[PDB]
Amino acid sequence: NCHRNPELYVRPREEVYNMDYVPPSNQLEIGRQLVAEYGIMPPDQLTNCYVCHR
Amino acid sequence: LSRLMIAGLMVFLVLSLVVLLAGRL
Amino acid sequence: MQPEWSGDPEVKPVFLAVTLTGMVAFLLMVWLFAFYW
Amino acid sequence: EAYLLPGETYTSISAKIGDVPLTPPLKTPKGWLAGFSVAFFMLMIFFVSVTWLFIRGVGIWGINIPVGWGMDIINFVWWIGIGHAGTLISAILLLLNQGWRNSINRFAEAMTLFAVACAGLYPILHLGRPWLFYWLIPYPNTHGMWPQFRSALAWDVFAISTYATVSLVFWLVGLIPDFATLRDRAKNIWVKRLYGIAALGWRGSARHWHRYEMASILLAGLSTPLVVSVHSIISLDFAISQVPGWQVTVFPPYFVAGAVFAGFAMVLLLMIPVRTFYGFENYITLHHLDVMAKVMLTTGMIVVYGYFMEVFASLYSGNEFEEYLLYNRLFGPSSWAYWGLLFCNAVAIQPLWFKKVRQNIPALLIISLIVSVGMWLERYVIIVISLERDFLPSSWDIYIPTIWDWSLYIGTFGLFFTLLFLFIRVLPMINIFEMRLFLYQETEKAKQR
Amino acid sequence: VYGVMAEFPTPEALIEATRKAKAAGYTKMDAFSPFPIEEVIEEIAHGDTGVPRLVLLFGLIGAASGFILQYIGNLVDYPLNVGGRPLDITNWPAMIPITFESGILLASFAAAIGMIVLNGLPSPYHPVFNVPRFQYASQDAFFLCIEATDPLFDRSRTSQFLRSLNPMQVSEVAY
Amino acid sequence: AQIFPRNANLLSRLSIFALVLLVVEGILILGVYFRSNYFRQVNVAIEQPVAFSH
Amino acid sequence: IPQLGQVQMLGLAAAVIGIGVLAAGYFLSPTSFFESYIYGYYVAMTIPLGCLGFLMVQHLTGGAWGVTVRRMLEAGAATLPIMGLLFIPIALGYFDTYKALGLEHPLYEWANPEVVTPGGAEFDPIIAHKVPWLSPLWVTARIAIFFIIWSALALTLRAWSRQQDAGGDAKKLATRMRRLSGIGVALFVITVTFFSFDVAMSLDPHWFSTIYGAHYMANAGLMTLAFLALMMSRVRDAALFREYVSVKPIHDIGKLIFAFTVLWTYMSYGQLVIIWSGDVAEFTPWYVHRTQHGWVFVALALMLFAFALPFFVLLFRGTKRNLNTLATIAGWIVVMRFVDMAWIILPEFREHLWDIAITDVAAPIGLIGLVIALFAANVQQAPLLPLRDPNMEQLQN
Amino acid sequence: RDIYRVGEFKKFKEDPKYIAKEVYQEEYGRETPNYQSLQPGDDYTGRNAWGMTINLNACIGCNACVVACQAENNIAVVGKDQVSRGREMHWIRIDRYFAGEDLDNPSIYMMPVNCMQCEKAPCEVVCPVAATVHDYEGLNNMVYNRC
Ligand SMILES: CCCCCCCCCCCCCCC(=O)OC(COC(=O)CCCCCCCCCCCC(C)C)COC(=O)CCCCCCCCCCCC(C)C
Ligand SMILES: CCCCCCCCCCCCCCC(=O)OC[C@H](COP(=O)(O)OCCN)OC(=O)CCCCCCCCCCCCCC
Ligand SMILES: CCCCCCCCCCCCCCCC(=O)OC[C@H](COP(=O)(O)OCCN)OC(=O)CCCCCCCCCCCCC
Ligand code: HEC
Ligand code: HEC
Ligand code: SF4
Ligand code: SF4
């Protein structure tokens, strides 16, 4: 689910910040900008089997 | 009978919904 | 030819019960197998 | 001659066929006892072979890395292919208005179901992770994965499941009015309920018989293309593969013909004793066995034509690989099976052109036994020999079966014969109705001339 | 109170009887037989059965469901690259056999369950087993029972009509 | 009525319906148990040998 | 009798149109004439060989449908030596008569010198490997042998059923026709599979199929069944079809049309899914040449109008028990078999859907018109529907 | 068969593609083969497509590559019995082929054979649980847990 829609859960870095973070309302918008900004690859590559299983 | 169909399906519904709740117990 | 239950009063609520069976059981598999994780 | 011998009334049909079931279980004949004891012993050989298959793995078989499909897939194709002729009597002769199916179709449907139960274990058994057989079935999972559905084993799973279910359905609708007779004569009170819910209280009647013939003709119309396709798909698990002896375009009609051929051999080998030992000589006449030898002769010629097509494909082609296929089948290390194939399935079938050979019962039985053995040899030649020698000569190796392949084969014979013996005990082996209807049709032909 | 049965000996006697019956105007009857005579069924089970439209519908939707299932599974929900095979409608070969098998499966379920349901078949109890000789219906007897649902029915007039053409034994059947 | 009683029709219709419902219920049992919070140990505070407190 | 003369006149007019446009096609470019004649002879040979084989199948399997169309099957089988006389322009086409009649290359690549000669300019080794089997003397000897067996089979069965009108028939002469048809069915199967090989599958010698021939079996049988149902509708008022034939054999023949349509699409799908799924590059150029350059739309129209509509329309009772709409279905079947044999044969030398000349319509309609004219002449010379026969009572049920 | 292609340095110097041209003239009579294919595949244009190259001029039969791919990838050792059956577990094997005239003083040819990682793979189209599939990078994805 995250490897097919990474825009719903990606955050503007601050990965290790405490759990005071809340996902904003424009999660589709800011998610698409952060997906294109971090180089998050298309889901045809991230759902490949040798992505996870090896 | 049809009221037996309703009663059996409501028993199955209650027991199945209790089972669904028990899978999140 | 018609079936022998064509002119029976049970033919309305039994065949309503088959679809009320379908929309209970199949939607329960839909809830468990798609919306329950 | 006549497909039904005279001197027979509806009381006589129901008395002769109906009283082979509903006999007292302690009054059961001792020949049945001996046959069922042998079948029980071989079913225990099955259980031992399956136990050592599950514990140790599929490596107890003689399969190696070139031959990934050894004797297991051969027995699978043989056991599934036995069911074609049973479904032929069940459905195709029902469609073609053939008068010889009326005494056979119960036995034919029954051995189709039992050969299906014997075959259908082999896709589960040949895995080596057999507990994940349901992964080939499209089922809702938390993974979100699917079967590939372009594989021919993915077609096989749907194919054997649909074939098993339709042949079971045809057996049950074919059995409901004979259940209605056996309920009506059972003479023990508890057995009348048992055959009663089996019959569902069939109540043999117009506006029920109309839907009976209508649904049976129509289900025959459903199952007639179906068994052709299901054995075409059993062909297609070689015929889509890129092995030189397996990618042959003739394979689906040729496997269909080989299936009808081997199944007619098995119906011969298992109905000559049912005709002789159980006194059903009037119901299954000699003209019955004549016409069944004729249909086996038809399918044997189409199979010999398929062998010719293989020889023509290997000679006509300029490819090295088809030519070395024909050489290694003819003069290779496993070439014994191909020579026994042309002795068995080709030389021994030309006797069946002559009527006296067809009417001779010991000759007909032994020639049917050679048909079954050489049919098995044909599956060996198709699968194992083509997997022995492939494109790269470093990937060439001999296939030798172990004791466990033969153990599983004999055990599946035990499962088949056990299920057949319970069938001929509790249920009747000839359609009681549709023989009474055949008696009616015979005396009506004798009326209108 | 359910009806009156007739007990004819031979299938030809039952056929000439059922031709004599309802030519008097006694519609809505049901002849019993061990085997389909196809002449009571030709005459008084005349019409359209009802299972072929069921098998046509369910086989069509089964082939449609098998095609849609293969498409949704391998080309939409989890598009996987196998063999260099296409991921569009050009992958129509290697999608036909599961379509056919699903169509035949749903079609044969339709034929079985529709015949068993349209006949009212799963019914272990029926009134017409009350007769002292109905156990010979599946075993050598030919019955012609007419029913109380018929508009011209009355017990004294029916059983004297069923006696006029020569039976072994006519008798009323309780409910 | 020769073999079976009067409510044999009732019991047979209810039995075919009940067989369908127990097949559906057994599938529901298997699916629920394989997704259960007991099986995957979800929302279960698994006890550590020190009881660290995050 | 008189409607038979009407359909004979229509076939003669079709043959005249065909020979006129075929001679015009020789006048423009004789190679196009010869390849169109290859196609026209193949789709013309769908009638008499299927007629012969179905006559022998019904003599093996004695049915009411078989007695219903035995005489029409025997007429169609009687046209075979005239099919030899219509073959021999092809035999001139691939022999030493080349370098005359304007041909640039011979009609087959094995009939070519350079593609098979050792040390030649071409020396294509796939075609040069099969040079004993595919040489002009060998192929003419094989085809003439197959002609001899087919003419012997057909004329012997026709003469024995002509002797059946007198006597010695309720057990004699039908056992003789049964034995002759029984041996000949295997003979006919192997010889017409080999005939389909030498005529069609050797046009491109780089490719083979072992289901070819059986594909041609189903094509010939389904063309034959639709042809039989088509002119069964014309001779409805022959007074003897009204005396002994009812709509039950009509239902049987519509049933067999339906069965041969599904058997043919099973054969074509079997070849297609075998070659398509196992993507090996000696079997694949046949389907590369058949879905390229416009042939793909002919393939989809073949799948949609020769399987799906003919299957779905022929599930019902009316359109099988009724004879008029069964005739309309059969005419659509015959046209769709023409289109299918166009897809089978014409990609081997046309390379485009838009390259299909007027000769590729002239030769099928003309040679089918010759077939129909000789057929309807052969029905009229005998009484149809053999009245004295041991399989007569199945018409009376 | 056309498994190990051998040339000479003078004719390879004068024409590098002559090794295939002498093969394909005997097989097909054309200098360049035309392998038509029905299946499309994937295009792999803008992706990192991983490929292997093995020089038959350089490989000697050292067999260190087999031990390396054994050590890296946890390939188990089967006994003498399972190689007697023919069930050795080696992801890369060395093909030794002995081809030459007089066959008692022959030319010996070692060829490493790992998986070709087939873009149009016959080995993915047949396996029914979709356990060997292709990825974005074009390499065969054998999933042990789905087998
Ligand atoms: C390429 C694979 C496709 C194969 C598909 C199956 C083909 C064979 C099916 C036979 C038909 C059922 C009979 C019709 C019937 O009884 O109709 C009656 C009267 O009926 C009506 O008026 C209503 C018609 C619609 C409902 C009937 C069935 C339609 C749907 C059937 C299943 C659909 C599936 C595919 C979803 C009149 O017909 C008859 O008199 C009897 C039927 C004769 C059977 C013909 C069977 C030949 C099969 C060919 C073998 C092919 C092999 C080589 C693969
Ligand atoms: C698995 C085997 C292959 C199946 C192929 C399909 C078979 C055809 C399916 C439909 C059956 C026939 C349709 C109806 C019909 O015409 O049958 C009527 C007739 C008997 O009925 P009467 O009214 O005349 O009653 C006489 C007895 N009282 O049936 C026959 O006579 C049999 C016809 C022979 C069938 C020929 C089709 C087989 C196709 C050849 C397959 C071989 C493969 C070729 C390589
Ligand atoms: C253009 C022609 C079409 C191509 C045909 C080529 C293939 C030929 C196959 C057809 C032959 C059918 C079997 C003939 C042999 C036989 O003996 O069957 C006839 C029997 C005899 O009937 P009785 O009762 O003895 O004579 C009655 C006297 N009044 O009866 C039958 O009809 C049984 C038919 C069996 C049909 C199935 C077997 C043929 C096909 C199976 C192979 C399929 C391979 C793909
Ligand atoms: C969303 C919250 C995700 C969860 C759940 C999982 N992954 Fe993931 N992961 C995510 C993204 C957006 C990326 C990188 C995108 C890219 O450019 O590739 C990753 C990275 C991985 C990778 C790297 C492989 C690769 O990028 O090619 C893998 C193998 C990986 N994560 C493993 C993995 C596993 C096993 C997961 C289930 C527990 C998993 N990830 C979940 C986003 C998310
Ligand atoms: C990470 C994002 C993965 C991808 C891509 C794939 N697999 Fe996976 N798999 C992963 C997880 C986190 C799970 C859950 C473990 C569980 O069973 O809940 C799985 C599950 C499977 C399983 C079941 C494992 C088993 O029962 O033994 C299988 C067989 C499986 N997945 C197959 C599979 C295939 C074929 C994949 C390529 C298309 C695939 N998975 C990708 C992690 C990830
Ligand atoms: S495969 Fe073995 S012999 Fe070849 S280069 Fe690598 S290590 Fe050396
Ligand atoms: S399918 Fe893949 S792994 Fe298998 S042989 Fe071909 S390239 Fe190698």
Image (cartoon, rainbow, N blue to C red):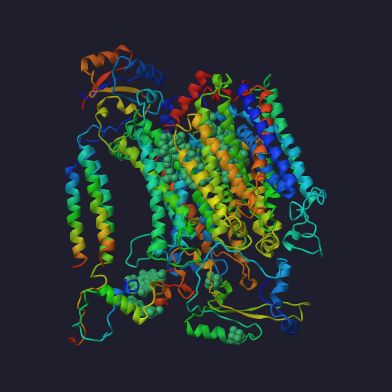
Residue nearest the viewer, comparing D167 with D185 = D167
Residue D268 in view of the camera: no
Up the image or down, E78 lies above or below E108; here it is below
Up the image or down, G125 lies above or below D174; here it is below
Query: Where's residue D277, x and y in %?
Result: 50, 38
Q: Residue at x 47, y 30 (%)?
A: G321
Q: Residue at x 72, y 46 (%)?
A: G33
Residue nearest the viewer, comparing G287 with D46 = G287
Instruction: Please indicate whether residue E120 sits to the left or right of residue H76 in the image.
Output: left
Residue nearest the viewer, comparing C29 with G5 = G5
Query: Where's residue B21, x and y in %?
Result: 18, 63
Instruction: Please indicate whether residue G370 sits to the left or right of residue E15 in the image.
Output: right
Up the image or down, G396 lies above or below G266; here it is above
Given the current orientation, which residue lies at the most extreme top position?
E164
Q: Say which quadrant the C terminus of chain D sits in.
A: top right
Query: Where's residue A25, x and y in %?
Result: 21, 74
Q: Quadrant of ligand 2?
A: top right
- Give the mark count: 0
Instruction: Please indicate whether residue C14 sits to the left or right of residue D306 in the image.
Output: left
Query: Where's residue E172, x and y in %?
Result: 24, 21
Residue G340 in view of the camera: yes
Up the image or down, F53 lies above or below E123; here it is below
